[PDB]
Amino acid sequence: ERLDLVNERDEVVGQILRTDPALRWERVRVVNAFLRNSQGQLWIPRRPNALDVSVGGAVQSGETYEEAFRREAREELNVEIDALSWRPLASFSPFQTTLSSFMCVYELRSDATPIFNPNDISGGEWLTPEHLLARIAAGEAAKGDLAELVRRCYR
Image (cartoon, rainbow, N blue to C red; front, side, top):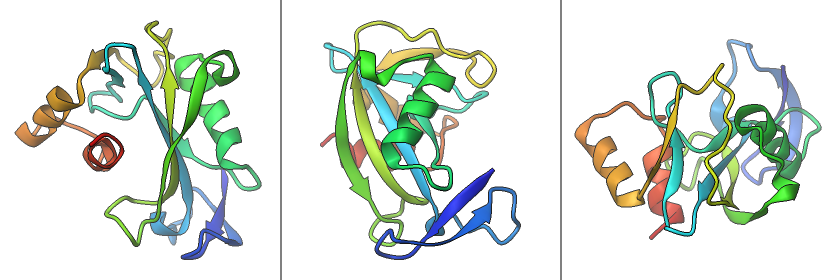
């Protein structure tokens, strides 16, 4: 429930409670990841009726980006990142883009559909970035940074 506070250089300068009313997302770190198969499709869950990244969540105080990634992947998708191929896709700053927080975006490789945790995900589907962006453009519900992450990370 506690998060690290970071400056413009993504350097830790303090801590804050996740539920603190003074919380500012541009002052904290999150992780986001996309699961992509050999068909070039991304597994997009519905989180729960809005489209979202395959795996995503805030980095806990004292935690590194990779550790947060491993944690969210297992709690949301029941996936062990160490059991699959993955890599840092990109890193972004909230002041250099229109993304909400400082973040590291990863890409997980797998052709298997995840045995996701139903508590936060109602279902998911393999979608091409083109079709996904089209739905967002149409007005279908989606996390605020999903479209930008897809565009910045994939062409």
